[PDB]
Length: 382
Length: 142
Ligand SMILES: OC[C@H]1O[C@H](O[C@H]2[C@H](O)[C@@H](O)[C@@H](O[C@H]3[C@H](O)[C@@H](O)[C@@H](O[C@H]4[C@H](O)[C@@H](O)[C@@H](O[C@H]5[C@H](O)[C@@H](O)[C@@H](O[C@H]6[C@H](O)[C@@H](O)[C@@H](O)O[C@@H]6CO)O[C@@H]5CO)O[C@@H]4CO)O[C@@H]3CO)O[C@@H]2CO)[C@H](O)[C@@H](O)[C@@H]1O
Ligand SMILES: [Zn+2]
Ligand SMILES: [Zn+2]
Image 1: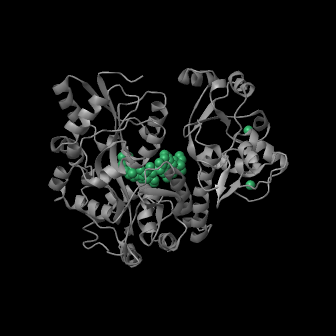
Image 2: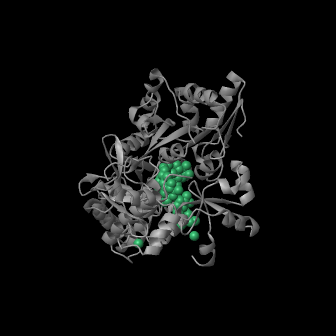
Image 3: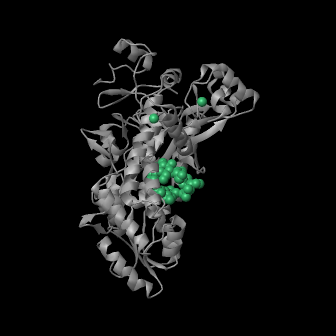
């Protein structure tokens, strides 16, 4: 049971331990309604567990891709913004929070990975992926490396894999085709071959994860990294003279990163749905509300048109938008979990050199489809 | 078998449609495409599994392929576990009123199998919203 006449919000700690709480304090001063902001560990996992029993927060903040699965499980309330409110936010952010024809969350901010470079080691970052091996040889002589980024998560390796033709699920006639996975094709094979060749030629290491890449870049050991707005704050503290730019091109085509929309979903079991809509629409999704959050930790490119225009002058946010425009919105369909694990395994297997790239990608398409077939054998009954 | 709002969903309706019996029906595994043994046809029906259509053809699943994929699913999609009593308290229903499938073979657990979990103090596992346990046969050898 969720407590009535109060608001409990779950958001990741690196989105700000003060920003959202401050908006919550303004809401309490105006309404008398107490707002509690919490940062539980593995909240994206804790939420579907507790919400299934009619418990949890009133509001949940996470990337939009997990929201389709929560809506399918009946965990999210359908959101009802008026036309005048829908007009204040970009249409593509509303599309990202639409599940089975209904709006299931409020869009907050737009994020995409960008190329982060050290201006002191590399005044002019490379425009193409193909020039990175020659850049690494030059930097290795100076006791440095060209690029270091998280190779463990498929979200991080996708910009390069998708560039020449890869895609998660095909989107045609306003619907995702769960039978059309774009992992086993010429494009994805070309991108992953380039990535694996970088590892084989010792320009990158297969074991490189989030922490290793972050430490290397922030200690000035690597000229470049690939990360998002959630990483900027630690780079600020490191005092590294950094630039945020457009991702390199592969085969003359832009890198296609996934696009994430940080979203605020209202718990279906909440007795405070009207208080929740009020807080989200009239307190958070305002220039004043987003500024309180953004000044604490940067959100990226906000869904709110008025404030996005005000922030666009930040070149890091302009790079986030350029990369997002060249990217692929993450499908919110529950079938994405099959995709994520299959691609994660493919990259590990191919990078290890224990399997060819093509065979790894062929196994990924087979494996993702096999998980979905199992779900079909079992039926929807729970 | 064009639309899913028409085509037979489970094995008993499929037999009725083809005008055959479960003792005679010829089915192949959706994964390996090998013809199911007569005992596997009976197990597919006991497991209350759905017929899967590919290129307008019905397919079942053999025992080995089902167990293989069920294991990969549990490994990747395991959410959390509860003791039987806590599960009963959560949904305010006895275990007999809940759909609990075997984590290995997918067979919906019998009241006796659910009771073994309570007696042996064996937890039930949540696999992305699905509650699972272990049947008598899989408790012996998976
Ligand atoms: O212990 C063994 C094993 O565990 C580790 O990883 C495992 C992990 O703990 C586990 O949760 C799981 O992860 C799955 C996941 O559940 C899937 O949903 C899927 O994740 C994708 C995700 O849903 C997408 O939204 C997308 O995530 C992006 C975000 O959208 C970005 O915002 C950004 O997130 C940053 C975030 O904004 C910040 O608040 C901050 O907290 O830090 C984040 C950055 O680190 O980046 C992520 C991307 O990282 O893309 C996700 C897909 O990459 O897919 C996951 C599986 O790949 O499975 C893991 C493995 O079992 C551990 O890493 C392992 O080494 C270890 O083997
Ligand atoms: Zn088989
Ligand atoms: Zn079993």
